[PDB]
Image (tube, rainbow over all chains, first blue to last red; front, side, top):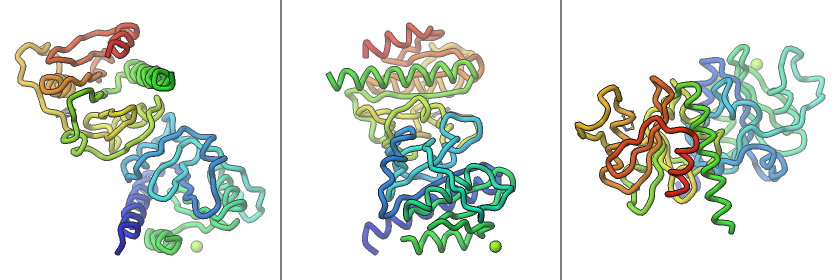
Amino acid sequence: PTPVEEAQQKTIEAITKAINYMAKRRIGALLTIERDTGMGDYIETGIPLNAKVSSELLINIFIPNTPLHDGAVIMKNNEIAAAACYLPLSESPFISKELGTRHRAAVGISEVTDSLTIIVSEETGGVSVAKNGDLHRELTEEALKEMLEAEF
Amino acid sequence: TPVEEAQQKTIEAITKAINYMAKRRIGALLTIERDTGMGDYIETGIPLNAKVSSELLINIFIPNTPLHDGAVIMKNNEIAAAACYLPLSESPFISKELGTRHRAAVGISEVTDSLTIIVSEETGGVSVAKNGDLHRELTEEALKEMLEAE
Ligand SMILES: Nc1nsc2ncccc12
Ligand SMILES: [Mg+2]
């Protein structure tokens, strides 16, 4: 594997470990991974981090009742670019009515970019992904990992 | 100048975070590298290389979280790493009521020119370690004077 490929693999591992921990504890989370459509306008709404990605940092960001926990984390390649970012809310009727603002923000950004967003529900611990305007719910750990590996 | 504005913004981020921690009696340990290189201690932690903000500093030190045990080390105006190991002082001249956070701060200050800021989890008191000494029960103004002097 090239260094770029190894680094990607270390980022996926960090992301999946953090999401798995938060799902178990019902820690709400909203994590958008920038792809080929630039997310600069949404990164500038948040607190800048420009940090190396770790499972530990991702977890600490989303602990309830803390300064960084509300809003989205936006990742650019192997960095956490910013936290507490604003994303636009989708009006799609295919978002389950019981879902709150994190899921609607995730679908929202996914309608205007090619990003992949991961959502952990604070109600149920369920893991979802928003991509291309669609929300995919109740993901197993394996499903999520495969989704991330496919996103490369 | 830009460098001057950056240093002031960093001082202001740190003091805001420390004041929030002190109010809530959240234990914290924040070392600022100076001329003596601290790469061997930075290596023991989780790498961040992150922009400083009061928000990030607070999120790092929340109790019962992955990053809260150990020291934050700052270098070149950025958070280099969190959850870092610092050497425990063996000095017999530290207040006997204090524990390992304060002895770690004094320890690193014995072997480097760094400045360490400590928030006590018992009292919310704020102290600074430098040159082997611990300066206790600092006000906000006192801490800012220390940072500006440094
Ligand atoms: N040896 C240490 N390095 S950081 C820290 N924090 C609390 C107690 C000990 C230590
Ligand atoms: Mg299903």
